[PDB]
Image (cartoon, coloured by chain):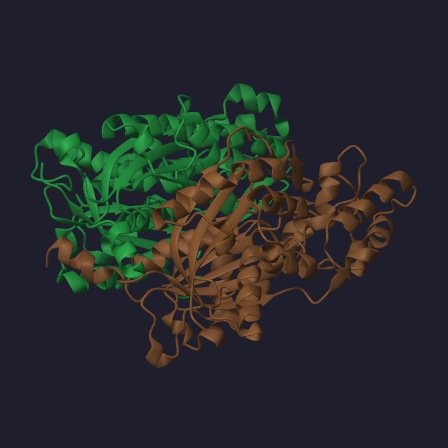
Chain colours: A brown, B green
Amino acid sequence: SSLDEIRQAQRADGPAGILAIGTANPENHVLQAEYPDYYFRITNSEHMTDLKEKFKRMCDKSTIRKRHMHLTEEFLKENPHMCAYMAPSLDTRQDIVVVEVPKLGKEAAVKAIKEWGQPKSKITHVVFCTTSGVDMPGADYQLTKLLGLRPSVKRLMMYQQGCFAGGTVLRIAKDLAENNRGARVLVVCSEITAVTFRGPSDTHLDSLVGQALFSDGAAALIVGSDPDTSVGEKPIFEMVSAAQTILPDSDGAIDGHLREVGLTFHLLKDVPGLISKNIVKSLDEAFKPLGISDWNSLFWIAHPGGPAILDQVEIKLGLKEEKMRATRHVLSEYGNMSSACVLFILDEMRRKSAKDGVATTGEGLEWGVLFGFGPGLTVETVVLHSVPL
Amino acid sequence: SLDEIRQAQRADGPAGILAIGTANPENHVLQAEYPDYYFRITNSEHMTDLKEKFKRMCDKSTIRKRHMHLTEEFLKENPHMCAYMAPSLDTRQDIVVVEVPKLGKEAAVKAIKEWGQPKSKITHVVFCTTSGVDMPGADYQLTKLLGLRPSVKRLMMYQQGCFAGGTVLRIAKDLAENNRGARVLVVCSEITAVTFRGPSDTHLDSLVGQALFSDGAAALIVGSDPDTSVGEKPIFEMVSAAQTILPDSDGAIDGHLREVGLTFHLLKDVPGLISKNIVKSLDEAFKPLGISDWNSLFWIAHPGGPAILDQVEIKLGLKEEKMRATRHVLSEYGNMSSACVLFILDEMRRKSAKDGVATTGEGLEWGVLFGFGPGLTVETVVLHSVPL
């Protein structure tokens, strides 16, 4: 009867858990070892011989083996304005991603829902995240339609977020699931680089780096509190806390602008140095309350923005080489899929843990940490607890 | 244990709106004079029949005044924004990526002043706009402009549309309620520089937008567990928040961000769809509370246009007084997209106080707030007033 009684009945009891993870990528893919030849040919830039050598080194240094790409050679042959460095091309790019981003998201969501094993009518909330296009109604609406979810799902559409937003969607889903009894949140991160693909320029090596790193993928979660074992729900990881911060002295480190030429990418500061110099503050804030100070005792998920971030964090903290294994495996096999990456890494970790026969979904360890890194410079820090295997 | 940590981490009570601040560009247009101004500045004075259509649209809009960042002087310098369809996204973005967080800041400063607490106590920022996109977003820019703590937890809601005043309340509710001590700065800021364009006699739906849309920002502080010992006091308390898609409404309102800016497209019958279905949202929200008399509620409805309000009133048998606050904001400010319903909350609690009625909700206990927009999406927030 009272507002207090209503509130306590309305909310969930326990911590939010990740109940299922599904992933998808465009079938079309490129091997990184072959990409410099392909890229300079399809962008009619073969005369740029010095720049091509720089791009070969970028691709070699990336540690990426394979990237999935919705954009095909045949499509680009028909759309040379997307192969130029800077031609009017937003409309064409939007035409692609407003359709393909929810479609790829749906593919991942179907897999998550299959693992979860529950009727889709039990989904109460949808969180859709992309950095690839914008439209109204949004991709959240399109996903809802494609999946045939209840019209009364509570949707949140996260557009133009950037690379930290795999952490952001966990932070969002945590509060939705924990504050609402029975809530089951479908989380989808879906990224298609048709908005950022463009030809090379030797006066914009930061843009060129993006053409070596960024790739396509989608990941989906079901998140909820108070799992129902009787119907086959089983958490994989439990969330404990989620934080976000802006690093000091990082203004303009990573900017992205949506323009008539598509989405442009700018780097102005040493991103690996900024992250490695400041990450301990985020670890202490997250783990000091738990009495944890040994960062090698945690299972690790880090957004693989590039290999230098991972290498410099590993050195700065004295991490064992094994700690970044799952992260690096995803970077190698998929490249930088922006917001989706950390969710692929959670999937990799729990799957490898099961294959290897260790004690928990987090490489046999109890506590873990997930980091998103992106424009701001923003760091998202999520504290996770594993589940026994 | 994790369960113990969870109990300590979360808040106890319902989320309240602790402060409301609003702002608009100083520049404004009187609706009575807009058809002449608009058809002049868009080089369309020869379009005689179309101007008459636009005059009737403006006359029927019930809008008296709209605030507009875009000035005549600026538009004279930028004829490509005055065309119906010319490449102009870059110019529009250049405006709104700066001006949207600036206007938001003006509203937020007022909300923070009313709240009366140190800005360091803000833990979360929710920024909502339909006017431009950028990385980092307007949430980051606002955080910087206000000098908030670098570790505020931000959510950037871009390209949301007209229902999102309801959406930000729904978001802020869960943030505040699930996090002990959380104090959420909510800002909706809209500038129509992305949608302004010249007329076309084959796109009368676009022309409607030119009669209705306007600029403004609103800011809230939202939190649970108000501390009276430092002078916090809720204005309204949130009880539940829902969202739904109306049946048979696919494609009613679409909006695309293109090289020509943001374009809007209307199909079907939006006032009809909303009014035919709104009772199902009211029943879902209020049947668990034992409430069925919709005239017993205080009302906030997104004033997407006058026909929505008129047809909801007729369908539900609402007394003429119910939509007073809503219509006042529509008259004085026009359709400020996501910010409107927050202006209407402010209008309602201020009028209530000035009139000396018993509560912030026109003397009534229970209320409802509706956002309407692309989907067709309806957001439904149940509110409880506070005694005056």
Taking the spot 43% from the left edge, 31% from the top edge, the residue there is B142
Position of the C terminus of chain B, as image quadrant, is top left
Q: Is B164 in front, or is B185?
A: B185
Horizontal and vertical percent position of residue B48: 53, 34
**Residue B217 in view here:** yes
Q: Above or below — where is B243 with respect to A389?
A: above
Q: Position of residue B208 (x, y in %)?
A: 46, 42
B125 sits left or right of B251 in the view: left
**Can residue B250 be spotted in the picture?**
no
B161 vs A328, nearest the viewer: A328
For the N terminus of chain B, the quadrant is: bottom left
Q: Report the side of A385 relative to A138 (left or right).
A: left
Please tell me whether residue A118 is drawn above or below residue B358 in the rendered image.
below
The image quadrant that residue B284 belongs to is bottom left
Observer-nearest of A297 and A347 = A297
Q: Position of residue B21 (x, y in %)?
A: 29, 30
Image quarter for residue A239?
Answer: bottom left
- Pinpoint residue A62: horizontal percent, then vertical percent: 73, 50
Outermost residue, bottom side:
A230
